[PDB]
Image (tube, rainbow, N blue to C red):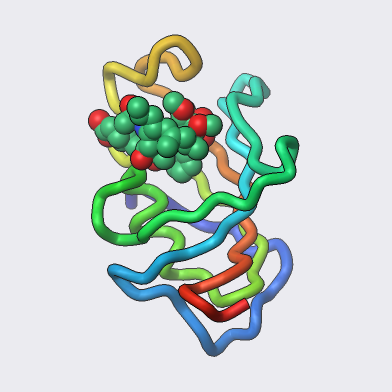
Length: 111
Ligand SMILES: C=CC[C@@H]1/C=C(\C)C[C@H](C)C[C@H](OC)[C@H]2O[C@@](O)(C(=O)C(=O)N3CCCC[C@H]3C(=O)O[C@H](/C(C)=C/[C@@H]3CC[C@@H](O)[C@H](OC)C3)[C@H](C)[C@@H](O)C/C1=N/NC(C)=O)[C@H](C)C[C@@H]2OC
């Protein structure tokens, strides 16, 4: 529904994030017009977040637990599961579909 996932490279197929876990992710975020609005890869800084607890947009909270540890995937996120009608000024317009390349590098202490 609000997020769908295309697998690019498989993870270990065994370890999946659960609600409340902390995950480490490398990502690149783009608009559908091609604009890159952010990239942890470009700043060489893996991004850590608790998953499933609303600290990140819903598309991440729902999509990331579907990935196995080590997986590279692309999340396509509808506005309802992203920043909605307001967007995120100044970088994400209202009603933006978001495209995230995501690599699941760690779950809690597992790498
Ligand atoms: C003072 C606070 C700053 C504080 C910033 C940091 C700790 C730095 C951290 C690395 C954020 C990134 O800095 C390079 C940027 O990430 C993006 O570039 C990105 O790629 C992007 O979309 N994301 C980053 C990677 C994961 C997916 C997604 C995300 O969910 O991000 C969290 C966020 C903005 C949550 C909103 C929470 C509000 C609520 O209304 C909304 O519901 C709809 C959701 C974000 C991790 C938040 O938890 C922490 C912060 N937030 N600023 C807030 C809350 O205003 C977005 C577009 C903008 C972010 O810089 C402003």
